Image (cartoon, rainbow, N blue to C red; front, top):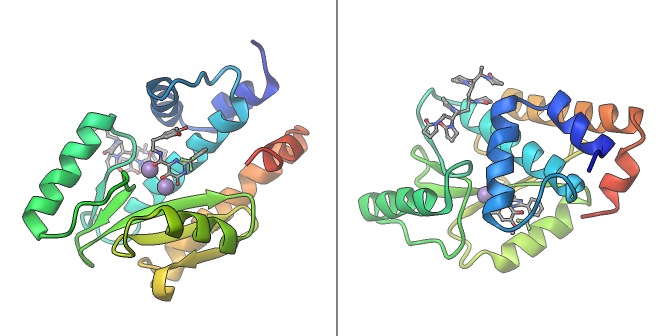
Length: 180
Ligand SMILES: C[C@H](C[C@@H](C[C@H](C[C@@H](C[C@@H](CCN1CCCC1=O)N1CCCC1=O)N1CCCC1=O)N1CCCC1=O)N1CCCC1=O)N1CCCC1=O
Ligand SMILES: COc1cc(CCNC(=O)c2nc(-c3ccccc3C(F)(F)F)[nH]c(=O)c2O)ccc1O
Ligand SMILES: [Mn+2]
Ligand SMILES: [Mn+2]
């Protein structure tokens, strides 16, 4: 299939993230060799969720994204049946042991207002916290509770702009922006 996008994704992202994104797409019936704009997106979403869980305490967060569909649901079942939190209708990305809430992490190429609105409309009940990031450095969280301190969030924003820069340098940012 070739694709300059696929070669950049493997050269830019972590091999474990590329493997986990590859498993995620094939689990849902999509091939990273054609859906290359997607391929770069789940890799970006995966890394952001991992940087997010790294922020704060060495514990604090339980990672839901990156697991198999069955295993990820088994964890939220244990989390709900232990803390009494209501079962989310859709698979979240993390769970905050410090704030007792699930987190839905979003990485968009639009403004943070639309993606939040689409995610909040799909999110069954506003119990699950929503945190949105953008490739332009913007961010938006539920009730302005951004969970982490400014330092950890600033690097996620910095890492996002480096990906956008490396992609525009390879003439791949235009097709990536007009695909979401
Ligand atoms: C070198 C360093 C490595 C990162 C790794 C970490 C991702 C993540 C790893 C796996 C564990 C694998 N499986 C398979 C199933 C059971 C299981 O456990 N998964 C994925 C699902 C949840 C999970 O646990 N882990 C492991 C420890 C905590 C964590 O989040 N992270 C976090 C930053 C980006 C990244 O990749 N580590 C290791 C600890 C410190 C650290 O940063 N890297 C790679 C590039 C950036 C970086 O620092
Ligand atoms: C069928 O679709 C996919 C579904 C999954 C499993 C669960 N998915 C998520 O948890 C999730 N996915 C995205 C995302 C990323 C790129 C394109 C589209 C989306 C989505 F908004 F449509 F879903 N962004 C998030 O923030 C997020 O939490 C895995 C891979 C899939 O391609
Ligand atoms: Mn997810
Ligand atoms: Mn998400």
